[PDB]
Image (cartoon, rainbow over all chains, first blue to last red; front, side, top):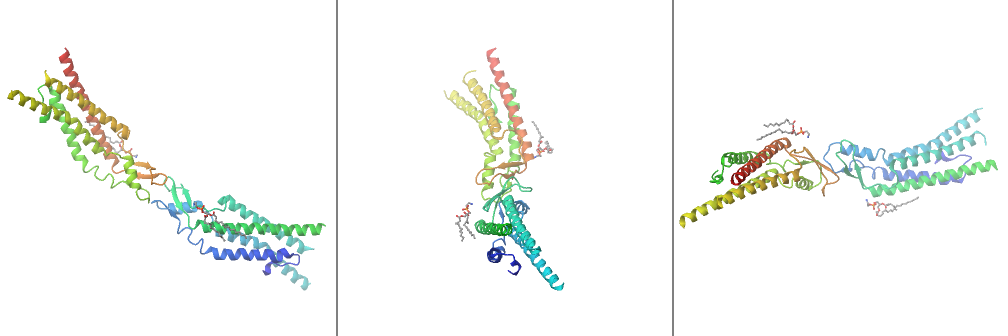
Amino acid sequence: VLGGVNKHSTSIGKIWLTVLFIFRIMILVVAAERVWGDEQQDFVCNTLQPGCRNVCYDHFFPISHIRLWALQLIFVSTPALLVAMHVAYTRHERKRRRGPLWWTYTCSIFFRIVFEAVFMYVFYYMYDGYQMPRLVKCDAWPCPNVVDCFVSRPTEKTTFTIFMLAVSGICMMLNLAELCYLVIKVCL
Amino acid sequence: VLGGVNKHSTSIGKIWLTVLFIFRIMILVVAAERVWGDEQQDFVCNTLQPGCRNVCYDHFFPISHIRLWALQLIFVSTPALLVAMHVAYTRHERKRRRGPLWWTYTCSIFFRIVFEAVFMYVFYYMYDGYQMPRLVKCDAWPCPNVVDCFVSRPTEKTTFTIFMLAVSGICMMLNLAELCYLVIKVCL
């Protein structure tokens, strides 16, 4: 909350973006330890081959969904943290002894859009959609031929994937609107 | 032994065919209860699906090898048994009150060749050779995808298959030679 206020921030940055960020954190907290807790423990494969469970789970879930969202939240909140420290350092120096603050705030907004876009592209490149399947067919060594494996709670995981994707898309739109608001105001 | 002697039988029928028939029976006796005893019990499939062991074994071994050879021995010894009863019935009637005996003996030889050839063709139509595989890949319902299954004692079963096939082929040749001996003698 505190690390989201600047003298150049409009109502969108002060209120709507701050609420959405808290919204994403709250959803992640309630859906991490309980929904994705038994992702590998309850991954059931129809085989007698030792080691097939480990390789098939790792093949279809190279990075867990909750870990991807945790990384995204850390990345998109870094530019806001950098701006706050720069403000304090400048405020300390000014007392001791647009402008520079305008460029730092504008640059932070640009990096928030880039980090938001990159993480959703990685999601689509890696899981080709939002729908988690009930069944996966795995043929990696040492599994013989093709082995059927069954995912834990596919429907609940699909529902939360839609929530995070939708809010992330809304956050990118709000950041874009704020960037356009600052550019046109200084230009015209 | 007794049911293999007729007044029209040459040395081949009296000696060589009788020894070969005893040879096949002796081999079958020592190789039935011990080599094929655990054919299904030691049939191991790499799966957790219930019922996959039953359907895959039945798919690849519709009739056991030993049961096929037992049926063949019964069939090829039937014409010899029929001839012996006809001789006793004729001998009883003659006392009570070439020729007919020549045709009965000749017909029995012809049926022995036919039964021998039919059972060998059935073996090749059903198992496409004498080599028993170590591994069979089975995809019949309810087995998921393709399941690996492992045969019990494939090498020992292959060795006895060669023995029975070789002796059956020799028995067919000897029967053919005896048939030609009788035909040319009566013709010329």
